[PDB]
Image (cartoon, rainbow, N blue to C red; front, side, top):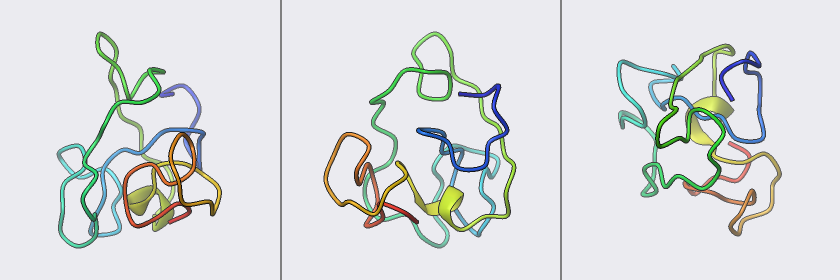
Length: 87
């Protein structure tokens, strides 16, 4: 997960708000994040038991709110952690 950039990746969320995205800690409320904190379903680098780093590239709205990529509210790359599938 960490060697891309990242713009909007298959799974790479650093933090949340205010529109940051990273902060000095993972997840971290201000500001929006509703309920789902970080349940580790996809063990690339940032989700990781003996891995885990953190990289920050756009402003951003979607990379402060989102877990997955498409506008499809369910689970397993669909609506992974907010009220928010795309944002």
